[PDB]
Length: 204
Ligand SMILES: CCCCCCCC
Ligand SMILES: CCCCCCCC
Ligand SMILES: CCCCCCCC
Ligand SMILES: CCCCCCCC
Image 1 (cartoon, rainbow, N blue to C red):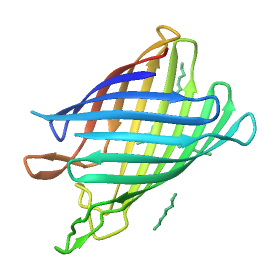
Image 2 (cartoon, helix red, strand yellow):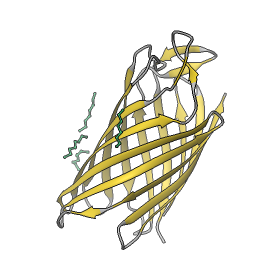
Image 3 (cartoon, rainbow, N blue to C red):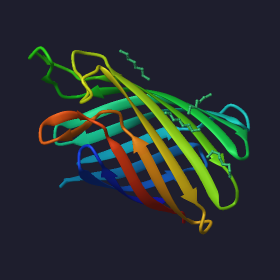
Image 4 (cartoon, protein in one colour):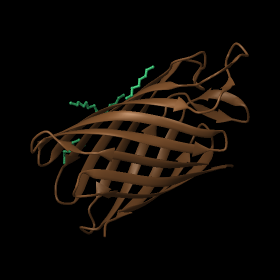
């Protein structure tokens, strides 16, 4: 599947575009590659996991998200648990440890590693043949002496996605995210970060 997404961030006063290609294999392997651009008025991420079928409803996915930026490489081993409660309702939970392969100045001025503990919760609800609603909730916290742009050692994200199944292989969507007070505009941080996004996913 190919996903193209454009987004506006209200606190950062910035536009971002994501181009993403993802595929599940019948042997259980799954992978994704994406690029994200950032235009104030950049990253590449590779994700791989393996789907362990516990039964017809339950799947465990050991995986890793590798994140490439100009600062360097960040490795995010994870485990995701997925439950298809019904054909129309799926729940998911993931814990990921984001470990930076590069050292950065911490809040005390010492060189350390800005590693992160990250949890995501997922609910996907196929409302009817036309629409699917998905919510992803996220909590991450710092392992070491660093902070987020909200002046805390932790922050949240909440992503709300409405997908319209126009075609069986074309799915336009709209999305609203609240990314905590993590907006940064001209060195000034602690801004409310609303995120408004529109995209479309294309199946083969
Ligand atoms: C899923 C990998 C677990 C890594 C946790 C490390 C905590 C210091
Ligand atoms: C068994 C996983 C529960 C997922 C919680 C959903 C939070 C949006
Ligand atoms: C179609 C009306 C029910 C949809 C609400 C469920 C959560 C988005
Ligand atoms: C079912 C949608 C949940 C919305 C949560 C909003 C949290 C402030």
